[PDB]
Image 1 (cartoon, rainbow over the protein chains, first blue to last red):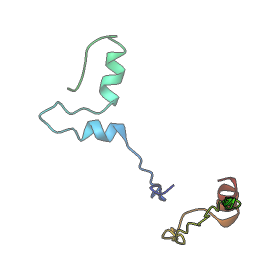
Image 2 (cartoon, one colour):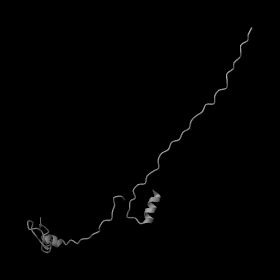
Image 3 (cartoon, rainbow over the protein chains, first blue to last red):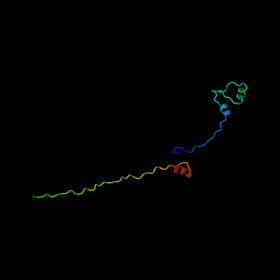
Image 4 (cartoon, rainbow over the protein chains, first blue to last red):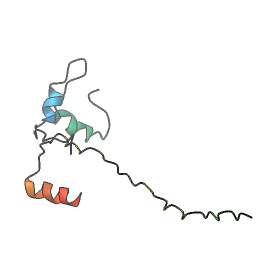
Length: 49
Length: 49
């Protein structure tokens, strides 16, 4: 109890289609729309790095 | 012809014992600390302690 103090409770939304869409171009940038719907149709492969 | 005097020893002294006391100073209060708990809870805590 000596060391404990009230901490600032914060919340942040992360948009994963933005975190992948904004990926630095030293990795291949991609929006999830065009790889989800082909790595299902092929059942195979990869995107990003 | 002379009969000597029959000198006779006195009672033993009462032995006596000495009983002395010891004294030690008054205590000292810690520095008070202010904490995140409303009084009824910190009181149930301290009372338990």
